[PDB]
Image: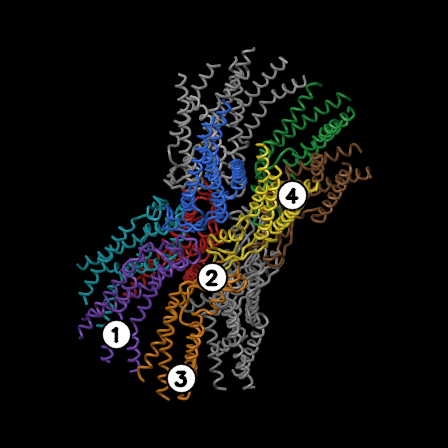
Chain colours: A brown, B yellow, C blue, D green, G orange, I purple, K cyan, L red
Amino acid sequence: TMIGRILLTVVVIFRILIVAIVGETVYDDEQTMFVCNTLQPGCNQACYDRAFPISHIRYWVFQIIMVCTPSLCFITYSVHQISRFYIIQVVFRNALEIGFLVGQYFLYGFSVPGLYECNRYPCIKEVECYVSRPTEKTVFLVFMFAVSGICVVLNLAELNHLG
Amino acid sequence: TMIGRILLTVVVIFRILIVAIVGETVYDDEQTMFVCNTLQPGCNQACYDRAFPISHIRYWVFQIIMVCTPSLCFITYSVHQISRFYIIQVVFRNALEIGFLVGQYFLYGFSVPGLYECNRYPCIKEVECYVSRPTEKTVFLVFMFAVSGICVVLNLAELNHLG
Amino acid sequence: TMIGRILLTVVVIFRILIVAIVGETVYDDEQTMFVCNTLQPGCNQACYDRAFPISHIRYWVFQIIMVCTPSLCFITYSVHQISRFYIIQVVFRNALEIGFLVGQYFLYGFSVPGLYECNRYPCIKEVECYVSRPTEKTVFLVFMFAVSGICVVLNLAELNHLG
Amino acid sequence: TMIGRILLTVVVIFRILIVAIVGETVYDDEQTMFVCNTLQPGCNQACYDRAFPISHIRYWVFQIIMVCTPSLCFITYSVHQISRFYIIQVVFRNALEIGFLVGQYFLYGFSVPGLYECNRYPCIKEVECYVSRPTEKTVFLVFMFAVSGICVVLNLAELNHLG
Amino acid sequence: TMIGRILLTVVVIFRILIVAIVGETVYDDEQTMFVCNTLQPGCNQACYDRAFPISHIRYWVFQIIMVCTPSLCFITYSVHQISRFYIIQVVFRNALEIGFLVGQYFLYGFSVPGLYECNRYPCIKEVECYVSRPTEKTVFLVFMFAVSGICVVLNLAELNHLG
Amino acid sequence: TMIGRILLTVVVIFRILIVAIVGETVYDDEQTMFVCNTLQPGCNQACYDRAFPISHIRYWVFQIIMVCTPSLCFITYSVHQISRFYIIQVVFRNALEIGFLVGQYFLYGFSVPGLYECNRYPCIKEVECYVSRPTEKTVFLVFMFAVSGICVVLNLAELNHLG
Amino acid sequence: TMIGRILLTVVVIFRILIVAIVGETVYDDEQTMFVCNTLQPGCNQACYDRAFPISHIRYWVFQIIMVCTPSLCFITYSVHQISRFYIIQVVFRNALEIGFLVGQYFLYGFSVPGLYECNRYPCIKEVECYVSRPTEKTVFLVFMFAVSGICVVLNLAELNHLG
Amino acid sequence: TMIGRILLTVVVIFRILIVAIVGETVYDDEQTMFVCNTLQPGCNQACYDRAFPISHIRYWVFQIIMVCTPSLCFITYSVHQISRFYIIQVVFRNALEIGFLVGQYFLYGFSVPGLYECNRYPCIKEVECYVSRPTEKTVFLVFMFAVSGICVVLNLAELNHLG
Amino acid sequence: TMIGRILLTVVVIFRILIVAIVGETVYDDEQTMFVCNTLQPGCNQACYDRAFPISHIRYWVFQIIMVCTPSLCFITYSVHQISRFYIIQVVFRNALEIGFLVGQYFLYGFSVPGLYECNRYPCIKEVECYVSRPTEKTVFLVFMFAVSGICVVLNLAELNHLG
Amino acid sequence: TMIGRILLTVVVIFRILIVAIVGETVYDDEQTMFVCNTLQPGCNQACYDRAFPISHIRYWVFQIIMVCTPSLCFITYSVHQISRFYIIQVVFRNALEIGFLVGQYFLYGFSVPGLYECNRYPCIKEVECYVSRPTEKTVFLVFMFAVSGICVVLNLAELNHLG
Amino acid sequence: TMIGRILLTVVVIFRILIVAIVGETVYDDEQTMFVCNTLQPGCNQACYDRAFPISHIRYWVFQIIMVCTPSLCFITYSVHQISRFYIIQVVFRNALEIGFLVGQYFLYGFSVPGLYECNRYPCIKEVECYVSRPTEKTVFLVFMFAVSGICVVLNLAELNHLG
Amino acid sequence: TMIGRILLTVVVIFRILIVAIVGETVYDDEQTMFVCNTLQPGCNQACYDRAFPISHIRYWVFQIIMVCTPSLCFITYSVHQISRFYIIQVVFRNALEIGFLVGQYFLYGFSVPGLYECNRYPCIKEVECYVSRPTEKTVFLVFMFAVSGICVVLNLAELNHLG
């Protein structure tokens, strides 16, 4: 139960670094290079909005920030100043990380396809649109799912270790 | 009344982080991707100005800065150097946060629609225009309203605790 | 006369923060989204230059920097090292802030209109041009005038307090 | 065996500096200046995605971050607090760097050509496309391969020195 | 001779701040908004290059950096460790600042006109071109000349004070 | 032999500052404002690549970083902890700086012309292309050559002083 | 009753000549120079079709041909070969010319306006369109109405003369 | 049975004149003003070809020429030179005119709609296209059907008169 | 009085030939090459219509046809079949030709200028437009006025000869 | 053998009329509406030239003119003025018409496809192009083949009748 | 003096045929393919009008018509009905043809250059423009001058023959 | 010598018909579909003028008209009214037709290539241009040469027959 802590800390820092340094620049051109075969004004806007409601990078930043709140609470408490608080914050972290992983699976799945079929007003009937960087975005998706799985496993390990 | 303080501090820091890190980049393309069905020069400018008089991110930055002024005053006083000042600053913070929440509701409501109908000069009669990222902007609106509600509840809690 | 100092310091810091964080990005697209109804090359340049000779944000940065010079002089003097210097620097600050407020009123007034009428070479006769974000720019103008008025009042207060 | 350590540290810092300061700006225009001889919408997207699945700079940042994890683990352990850990981390670093060099060779090779032949839907039959900055990108490839080879040699040196 | 030093330091810091914070963004669009009445490829490039050989902001940054070298030399000497060095560095600073002011006058003069007449290959005969932001650039020119004049006067003051 | 050290340090810092602050922004538009008289797709890419294989700013950053490696080695050695190392590092620095100056002369020469003649596929026969900011780039070239010459002279001075 | 015949023949020939020689070339550009303020494909087609269902020149050619049929019948009869036929053909000509004049008034009126307001699918709401050569077309309308009135009067004259 | 001949001759000449003088110029812009909402090359060609396989004016010219062949045969026979030939040619004319009227009904129907829905390669799925002058073309269709009906009735009249 | 008749006939035939052979092709591009400096849709149409209400060639064809009607009347009378008719038709021809010459002078004057100033809706304020072939059109105007003057003189000659 | 002559004359006149009146206007837009999916200048020209070397209408006019030469020769002979000439001209006409029918089959076949695949310089590899009015052109081809077959049969009939 | 008449008649008919059949189609694209290097609206119109005030074909048609008037006068006289009239008409024809040849030389000269230099408002300073078909137009000029010279010689021959 | 006359007349009429009916419409788009790979204004004009100085159809019309002049002279002579004139006109016709055939060979040769290489001002160095309908134009060239050869042979036949 000694190394588990060390590896959890290392995984957390690794995830933060990967998200902070490179992820902001794969998605930079997401809408400027999204294009549809049509002459109707506003169809690109409607179809992009329907294909990508919340961007991956926004979801990941939110998750990263929200999984660090129990630690901040514990730190503020101790600064004003314990084991019951430790138990409760561990429970809360476990719950939050399982919820976020499940939500990721339900929102995005495991792949980003290259074509999208759209039927939203003002587009006439169904139109075909084309995505930017699908392979790189799929690789990023899979990597993030793997890291979050590792973190879930480790936190369950420690929860069951204490009992 | 002990945990309330800790959670108020955590909510404040969380709100600042969310606004500072991601909000500047959802709104970056607000006017460059706003488009209207027309051939008249200046109609896009007039209709964008009428649809979005003050941007959300500007309003939120202003609110965040203004709700931290009583603390700065108290700090400057103590550095020159109390309970009466504490009472007064708590009262002022309560008033300011209720005012800002009410103003948010009256300025923006609870949703951002995808279409807008415009009848401002130099546009001839009424024209139809199309918005960028309405779903993401609606999600952001709802999240910010929820956070500000939490803060209002907590500050009223402490006000009534002291009495 | 005790609280006046504290509120002057708070107003100064508030003004600096508002100018530094948001003002650089309302004006970013000032000339790229300025457009005139014409086919003559160079008319957009001439009409933009005649409508907006010095930008608001440039004027405000200059004013903010210039109203902090007496403090720097006093600090450098004391570091080399007094009441006469205090008197003189208070007088100078008062004069500078009244001059800057008067100049603001004479340069810009109280509103930014949406249309502008231009008759400068190489434009043939008179042409009509269209401005970006007039409502937001008007709001910013009014807010800055109010803050500077508050500062003027406080400094006159202290000047007359000492006498 | 004394100088080997010093030169390994110098090589690592040199590599980090070269990657961090200049590499982000050779690749900035990679897709905006990629062009194909065609009139079909979406062909540029499909052909760019097939020619460049993962960008060099992304691969190099990932490798740089991943080769520094054993040191972070050792530091965290000692802070909580050894020779067995030293042995294991040396072994792991050796393995990781050999794996990354082999993967680089298998993904990219030793050159970036100026022409690319594409046959992916929606492109009709085979089309010809043109790359940006091939000579500079080839120079960067060769330099990075050389540096990583040096690092591999040094780490094997020390592994065999201890035995 | 006491206040002269203080005001010289204040003028130097003021000049550095003005150059560093705002000057980089008046000149940002210098070539993208330069336009000529012609259909010949390469004429805009040739005429811009002939009208503006070295940009003002480049000249000012170079001057600012070069007028601070004697101080760095004196500091490095004292750290290794005097009045003779003080004399020599004062002389050198005086000479450098007079040279730079004279060069500014000879390179640029006192105004930036709105029209420019060009006769360089590949332009056929003489063509007319149009400049961006001439009034703002003229204001900046005059302000910088005034500041440099103040600095020259003060340094001559101190030189003649010591003798 | 005392002042030589001081001036070498000052020259090195001056060179680093000049390269770091301004050079990144003269070359920013190098390819976006490069244009050729042709209707063939891909000719601009091929001709730009043949005219400018490695950019000046990349070469200068690499040289600056590489001429500081012996100092880092000496520092790391002393931290683990000498005159023999001093001798060797002086020799190495001399050699590296002479090599880099010779390479600069052989790669670029002393001027940047305004026209370039290109005959690379897919361009049909020979075409004429036009360069951005040739005068400013020539000035930068000459300045950098002068500085590097000064540094070479000083290092040879000290090498021969010790002997 | 003698001159009436002569003038009827002269009016008929005059009308035929005017229609045949010039009318085909006022209307030649009717749809190519019809333009609407819109970006919607197909709106110009729908609005032109609704504004001008049958062109004037088509209506006039049809009328001219149809008012000459009784004469052809009488000629064919006499060639095969009477007063009863004369009576009947006079009656028929009278009826046909009164019908055609009434239909002209009910289809077109007395003027062609320069603006037209359109609300047909696929146009969004109401749009404004602009007509070619309205003054010339109005002059032609009035002239043709006058000529047809003269012819009606003369034929009624002769009908009542015989009785 | 006397007038029937005269009216048949008059109807034939009237039909020829109407077709020859005006019909060539309603259809002149049939394909140049046919437009579809799409960005795919070749879709306009495929959809126009599927909507209008043989033009009305071509069909009518062919019919007019083919219904005059028996007369030419009879004339050539008599010039070389009968009642049996008269009978046979009357029979043939009757048959030909009934066949042509039936074919007209089966090819075109009674109206020309303003919209057409197309699903032919290379068009992606179904697209919407817009027709030129539908009301005028419908009027022409109905008029021609009426005239041909009159001719059919008259020829059957004479066939049954002889028996 | 003998040659006057011959020359009148020759002048009439000459005028008809000049109008019929060349005049239809100077005016062919009248509206396609008319251009105004503006970006407003419909302004070219409104300004062309206001500058040229009835084209010269239309006016001249109408005049030529109308001055030949008395001859046709006299011919038809004589075919049915005198000096009184001769007198009356001479009087009528004189009156018609004087009326047409006066109307020409009042409609068009003696020149066609190259510039036109327009202030009709939808044009904003006053705009400048440019005419096609003004010199050729002026030459044609003057020639036609001269010919019509000759004809007027001759007809008055004969009228006064008979008395 | 009596009717054969009459029907041959009727077929010849029918063919001439069909070719002369309508065929010139199906092919009018043959090259202006021919389009290929490419960005290479000159590819449309090369591919159109390879797909349609000699146009159908040119071939048919040439054939029609050449099959009437023996008659002109016989007429000129008789005007200067026989059975031997009749025999020879019949033989020649038979041969010419069989040759022309065979050549038609070998040049064009029985259909015009909608797509064409092109691989001629300057087109890169193989490109796809799209044809105008293929169904109408196929109908015309089949009709002309049928008529020419009828003529061949009749002329062989008469040749074998005389023997 | 016998053949001179015959050759004069043949030359006249030849000239009429050459002018009537081909000259109308060399000049058809005179203004549509005239182009100037400029971005100013109206400059093409002004420069074309100044370069070509009256077109060659207009001048030649006018001359051809005017040199046939004496014959028409003589014919009309004889129809009403001599040697004195013959003399006078010969004199007049001689004078007219010499005048027209001299005017041709003074208006046009002997060549049409490919470049033209223009300095008319609204063109800024002097601009360069490019002509269509200069070699063909020069050939036509020379041919017409030669023919008119032949005619002048022949008419002088006959004038001096009679005396 | 009897049939030779008949065949000469038939060949002449055949040639006139072929030239008059079809040749005017192969060359109609000669310059509108001529295109060069360049961005220089005026290069298309200069290169078209250098490639095609006099068009084939112009040359052929001129030749056809000029080879019929001796017949017109003989006809005019006989109308005023011989064997000597017959001899002379035969000689002249022979000479004219041989001259025209030789000139055709020297001006045009036997083929029209698809590419042309141009080096005329204002084109920079050498450019490549592309021709319209080369195969059809080559076929026309060869056919016309063959016909003119036949005519030459026949006229020499008759010349030598008389002797």
**Mark 4 touching mark 1, by CB under 8 A?**
no
For the image shown, how many numbered marks are present on the structure? 4
Report the amino acid beneath label 3. Answer: Val
Label 4 lies in what chain? A
**Mark 3 touching mark 4, by CB under 8 A?**
no
Could you classify mark 1 by the number of other residues whose Cα lies within 10 Å: few (under 14), some (14-19), or many (20 or more)? some
Secondary structure found at label 3 = helix
Mark 2 to mark 4 CA distance (whole Å): 46 Å
- The residue lying toward the viewer, choosing from L95 and C77, is C77
Q: Position of residue I9 (x, y in %)?
A: 25, 69
Depicted I154 relative to depicted G38: above or below:
below
- The residue lying toward the viewer, choosing from G104 and L47, is G104
Q: Which mark is residue L11?
A: none
**Corner quadrant of residue G87:** bottom left
Mark 4 to mark 1 CA distance (whole Å): 92 Å
Mark 2 — residue? G128
Mark 1 — residue? I92
- The residue lying toward the viewer, choosing from B141 and K57, is B141
Q: Are marks 3 and 2 on the same chain?
A: yes
Report the amino acid beneath label 2. Answer: Glu
Could you classify mark 3 by the number of other residues whose Cα lies within 10 Å: few (under 14), some (14-19), or many (20 or more)? some
**Corner quadrant of residue G122:** bottom right
Mark 4 — residue? A57
Label 1 lies in what chain? I
Mark 3 — residue? G90
Q: Position of residue A74 (x, y in %)?
A: 72, 37
Q: Is residue G75 visible?
A: no
Mark 2 or 4, closer to the camera: 4
Mark 1 or 2, closer to the camera: 2
